[PDB]
Image (tube, rainbow over all chains, first blue to last red; front, side, top):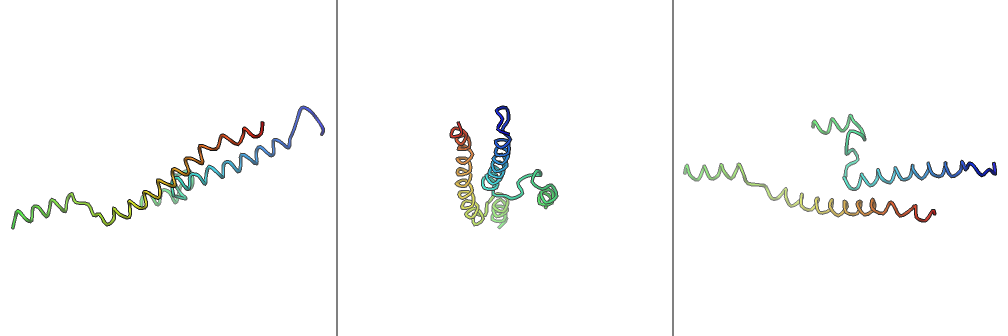
Length: 53
Length: 53
């Protein structure tokens, strides 16, 4: 509290910014690919099923 | 008649169905424009941290 060495609030704000940045890059993947399941990383079962089909 | 049948078979082997190709052309032009938009949005990501200094 009121300390020089540490600022927890900046850490929480930074992890929140990292979360919104990850959501942004995921949406960028959904537009540049046009697919909501573009790879096995998104969902392996539906992806393998659509691949075989 | 046999020569006409052989030419028809060569056409069945190689010829493309352009009616599918027109829809593919339209969808691919739209997908390319969306991909250029997503690429620009990905290129802009670095700018945000200049304002926090």
